[PDB]
Image (tube, coloured by chain):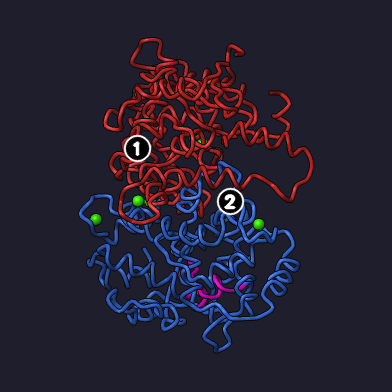
Chain colours: A red, B blue
Amino acid sequence: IEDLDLYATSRERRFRLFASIECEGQLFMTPYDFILAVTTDEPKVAKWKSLSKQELNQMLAETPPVWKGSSKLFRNLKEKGVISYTEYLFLLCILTKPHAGFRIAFNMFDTDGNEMVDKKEFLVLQEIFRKKNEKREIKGDEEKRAMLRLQLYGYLVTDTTLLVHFFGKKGKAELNFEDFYRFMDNLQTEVLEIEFLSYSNGMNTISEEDFAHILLRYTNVENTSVFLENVRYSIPEEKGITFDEFRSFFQFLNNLEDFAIALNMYNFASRSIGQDEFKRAVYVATGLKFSPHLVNTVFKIFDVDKDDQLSYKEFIGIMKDR
Amino acid sequence: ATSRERRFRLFASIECEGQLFMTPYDFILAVTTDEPKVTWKSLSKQELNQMLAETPPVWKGSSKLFRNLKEKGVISYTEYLFLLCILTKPHAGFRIAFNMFDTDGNEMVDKKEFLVLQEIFRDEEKRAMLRLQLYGVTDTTLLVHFFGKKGKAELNFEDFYRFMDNLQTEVLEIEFLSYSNGMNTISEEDFAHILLRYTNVENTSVFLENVRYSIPEEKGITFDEFRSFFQFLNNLEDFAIALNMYNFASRSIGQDEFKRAVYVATGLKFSPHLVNTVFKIFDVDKDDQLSYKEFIGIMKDRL
Ligand SMILES: [Ca+2]
Ligand SMILES: [Ca+2]
Ligand SMILES: [Ca+2]
Ligand SMILES: [Ca+2]
Ligand SMILES: [Ca+2]
């Protein structure tokens, strides 16, 4: 409850805010609750359904096998599934990875090198985070800390939607790199689709005012309203952003590092890039092809100086790394 | 002037046509030291062009190019910037830099590709005079070394890659040797101090005093260990990707996790001595674990 927030991290408070399933004191998110957790700010309604272990396992008995993955996995599993806190963290982490990172992640999992991931490999990290936070060095409020620990990790282990989806109902299936990649690619694409569609209202395009508005979640914009007032007046016509362009730009945001390397020669010289070699830098660094409309829109959103060029802290410096 | 331009002018030693240059030794100093110790020298275009006519071809490149060329070389302000940038790129970036030059995609770099991307980076009397000073077409050591003496050779990726690798290695060797005093290893304290130029460490003295008591017995860091670690620092963002969930969970890695994370992230294999040393330098909690705000948080973004 409100009691246990005072003992909790930001991420733990937010997990608890969006979670709706309790089973033997462990709290859970449904796939819909996760979609809301990543596309929304706060829930709209307050409450909180409590399951026994076998009504939960009937809820899971459906779960599609891994080969049924699609950007619509989580929306077809609307509320018929369960996600733990660790699993939540996993999914959040996926949302920020570049595609090459999927391989870094897979290799971080495959402790033994056979190029598959056991259920038991996959479970070691929930084991690691469970143990770590427990603090036998910090005294006081042990019972409330234990309750929050239970809420977040339980106490082989309660089956979950990702656990059954990945390793089957018996837990003996294994995951190769290709399925892992497809799960993370399909989840990135799902979250992007839900945001885009949340603004398109049935069109091919979202407005650039809505584009920029979504962008401000990724920025350290000191005054949010002054920046939106800058896009509304800098761009008197709206031509609209297509889904391909919106996906292009967020794939690029996950490859921002490689972009900084590419423009490093510019930043050593304190010089600003133009839109042509901004586009070309995006291509050679990321492999993505930005439309001239997308590039032009980014420039009108971020080029405050109004030179039709972008300096280091007009774009790259302003993006947050979380 | 920008910081970088003030430093270029302070370490520069050659004038030709009002145009200023660094010699390769002046670059070594500009990269390894804090300020010069003392003489200047003015060349004509053709004594500069013979001084350059000495320059070794690409296929004689080595970790010792810049020190064998001790003061028989020429480096402009732009080329200075280029080399700085070289020093900070990870090896995976080299292909991206090369492709940033190869406007036409033939997988080679003309002299004129190289010069077009430089040349884009270019009181009325004083601003103009300083503009002459940094930019002046005038041939340089890098132009002759890369594209031959009449510049119609072109540069394939193989030689580009080895040039920036060997320049990284040259600079690292000079710093290492500046501390080894003829031994096979540098001290773990001298290691820490060198690292400290890369950190946002508020109090350096207590930090060094902490490695000195954390490592009361001295084993040394070898050059392979030292180069590996500075290679890792240029690949830190792959490292952060690897540890991303530790950072999401507010959790600390142990040395085994840390070592294997370095491998999976970068491909580099740290000796257990190297890992133990990094831990003893940075694990300040003394939990034998590293939290985000002990290591990754502490590093500067190549400022
Ligand atoms: Ca395995
Ligand atoms: Ca601008
Ligand atoms: Ca990469
Ligand atoms: Ca070419
Ligand atoms: Ca620590």
Q: Quadrant of ligand 5?
A: bottom right
Q: Is mark 2 within 8 Å of ligand 2?
A: no
Q: Which residue is mark 1?
A: A167
Percent coordinates x, y for residue B253 in the rendering? 56, 54
**Residue A20 appears in which quarter of the rendering?**
top right
Q: Is residue B21 above or below residue A146?
A: below
Is A10 colored magenta in this rendering?
A: no
Q: Residue at x 72, y 59 (%)?
A: B202
Badge number at residue B124: 2
Q: Is residue B278 above or below residue B26?
A: above
Please, which chain is the residue tagged with disc 2 on? B
The furthest residue to the left: B106
Q: Residue at x 40, y 42 (%)?
A: A98
> Which of the pair B282/B159 is nearer the observer?
B282
In screen coordinates, is B39 left or right of A106? right
What distance separates the C-alpha of mark 2 from that of mark 1? 72 Å
Range of magenta residues: B17-33
Percent coordinates x, y for residue A278 in the rendering? 40, 40
Please, which chain is the residue tagged with disc 1 on? A
In screen coordinates, is B158 left or right of B188? left
Residue type of the residue flagged with mark 1: Phe
User: Would you call the spot at circle 1 few (<14 residues within 10 Å), some (14-19), or many (20 or more)?
Assistant: many
Q: Helix or strand or loop: what does disc 1 sit on?
A: helix
On the same chain, marks 2 and 1? The answer is: no
Q: Helix or strand or loop: what does disc 2 sit on?
A: helix
**Residue A251 appears in which quarter of the rendering?**
top left
If the image is split into quadrants, where does the N terminus of chain A sit?
top right
Asked if residue A174 can be seen in this view, the reply is yes
> Which of the pair A293/B51 is nearer the observer?
A293
Q: Residue at x 78, y 45 (%)?
A: A139
Q: Is mark 1 within 8 Å of ligand 1?
A: no
